[PDB]
Length: 102
Image 1 (cartoon, helix red, strand yellow):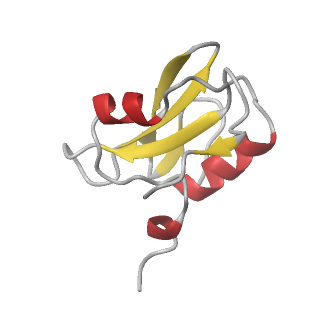
Image 2 (tube, helix red, strand yellow):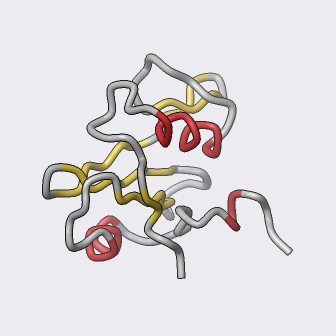
C-alpha cells in the first residue's frame, strides 16, 4: 500500500542533491527524477538532465499551489510532472524519461 505519489517511477523520495546527480549520469537530455528534501515535508526538487548537466528546479508553494516558475501552477506534484512531460513550457527540456526509482 502507498500513496499515488509514492508509486510514481520518477519519485525518489528523500535523496540528496548529490545522490540525484549520480542517478542522472551519464547525461541524457530529458532524463529526470523528483527528490524531496529532509528539511521540510513536500519540499521537492525536479532534477532533469539537459545539455550535458543536471538542472535543479525547486518547487515553491504559493497558497498551497505548486510552481517551479511563478507562472504556471498546479494543485499537486503529479500534475506538475504531467504538464512538463508533454511540453517544455519554458523548462530546459520536456520531461522525457523517468529515471526509475529502485
